[PDB]
């Protein structure tokens, strides 16, 4: 199946998922001088006070923290969105070195990593239905740069040796995703897609302008994870990012002047 190496990486994905060459693929480069300020954009509403985390999982392409989405516990609203979207999971994309790893770029600048908080539109009832709709998901993207440690990330870092290889999972209850957010919720937004297969064109992307800082020790622990399952030749889970895709007939809008 698909992955991030020479022979199964993003250049190959269109063969099994031909929407890879579609009209609203993600990620994209955010040209900040071309993105237009929209004064009609509302502030984001991030309501995570009741978030209920469940598990942390190595899925062979990232690690994921999954939440209870059977109720409106942790929801994203406002911004460019109409309706309520429930937080299902978050995961990251990162590099083998600090100068690459993010999926979106800002004036061609690459961050060391990128956090994706994945939400689905409750009017579609479940995420499987939502992925089939052009407004089915909203992914909140947050850049990571290397500098000071992010204290709200360390509980995640602490447990990664227990899910080194594909298929391993662990209890990861009582995690507060509010500890991963930057101060500002100013954002860019465009219509796009999932950045891994099935690459469905179902995502309103909301990318925050302010990155969070993480320490070199924290990102080091990401780079120690493995794509392989246990017992297979060890291939470090690094550079699990899709490069920027053609913007085509899309405009990126900014919530801030
Ligand atoms: N990297 S991402 O754009 O935030 C992403 C989120 C969810 C999914 C996904 C995969 C399978 C079923 C539902 C959602 C894929 C990519
Ligand atoms: Zn992602």
Image (tube, rainbow, N blue to C red):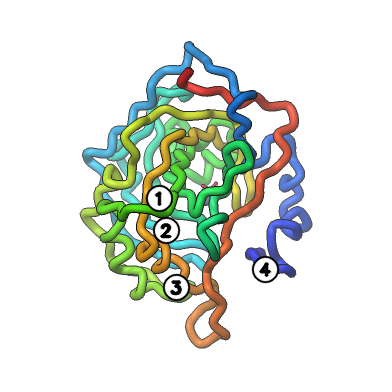
Q: Nearer the viewer, mark 4 or mark 3?
A: 3
Work out whether residue 86 or residue 215 is closer to the camera in this orientation and state it. 215
Residue matched to label 2: 64
Distance from disc 2 to disc 1, alpha carbons, whole Å, reads 6 Å
Query: Can you tell me whether the CB of the residue at mark 1 lies under 8 Å from the nearest atom of ligand 1?
Result: yes
Could you tell me residue 230's position as x and y percent? 48, 83
- First in sequence, mark 2 or 3: give its number: 2
- First in sequence, mark 1 or 4: give its number: 4
Asked if disc 2 and disc 1 are in contact, CB closer than 8 Å, the reply is yes
Q: Is residue 214 visible?
A: yes
Q: Secondary structure at mark 1?
A: strand
Residue matched to label 4: 5
* Dot label at residue 30: none
Residue matched to label 3: 224
Q: Residues within 10 Å of mark 3 (few under 14, many from 20)?
A: some
Q: Nearer the viewer, mark 2 or mark 4?
A: 4
- First in sequence, mark 1 or 3: give its number: 1
Q: Secondary structure at mark 4?
A: loop
Residue at the front extreme of this rendering: 147
Work out whether residue 182 or residue 66 is closer to the camera in this orientation and state it. 182
Asked if disc 1 and disc 4 are in contact, CB closer than 8 Å, the reply is no
Asked if disc 2 and disc 4 are in contact, CB closer than 8 Å, the reply is no
Residue at (26, 60) in percent of width and height: 155
Residue matched to label 1: 89
Distance from disc 1 to disc 3, alpha carbons, whole Å, reads 21 Å
Q: Secondary structure at mark 3?
A: loop
Distance from disc 1 to disc 4, alpha carbons, whole Å, reads 25 Å
């Amino acid at each position: 199946h698909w992955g991030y190496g020479k022979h199964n990486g993003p250049e190959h994905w269109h063969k099994d998922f031909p929407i890879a060459k579609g009209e609203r693929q993600s990620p994209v480069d955010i040209d900040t001088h071309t993105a237009k300020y929209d004064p009609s954009l509302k502030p984001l509403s991030v309501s995570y006070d009741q978030a209920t985390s469940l598990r942390i999982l190595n899925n062979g392409h990232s690690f994921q923290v999954t939440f209870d989405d059977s109720q409106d516990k942790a929801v994203l609203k406002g911004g460019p969105l109409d309706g309520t979207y429930r937080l299902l999971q978050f995961h990251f994309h990162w590099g083998s070195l600090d100068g690459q790893g993010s999926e979106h770029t800002v004036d061609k600048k690459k961050y060391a990593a990128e956090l994706h908080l994945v939400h689905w539109n409750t009017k579609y009832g479940d995420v499987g239905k939502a992925v089939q709709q052009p407004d089915g998901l909203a992914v909140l993207g947050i850049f990571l740069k290397v500098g000071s440690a992010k204290p709200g990330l360390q509980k995640v870092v602490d447990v990664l040796d227990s899910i080194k290889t594909e298929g391993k999972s662990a209890d990861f209850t009582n995690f507060d995703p509010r500890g991963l957010l930057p101060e500002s919720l100013d954002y860019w937004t465009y219509p796009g897609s999932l950045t891994t297969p099935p690459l469905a064109e179902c995502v309103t992307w909301i990318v925050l302008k302010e990155p969070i800082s993480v320490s070199s020790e924290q990102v080091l622990k990401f780079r120690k994870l493995n794509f392989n399952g246990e017992g297979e030749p060890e291939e470090l889970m690094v550079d699990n990012w899709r490069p920027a895709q053609p913007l085509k007939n899309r405009q990126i809008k900014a919530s801030f002047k």
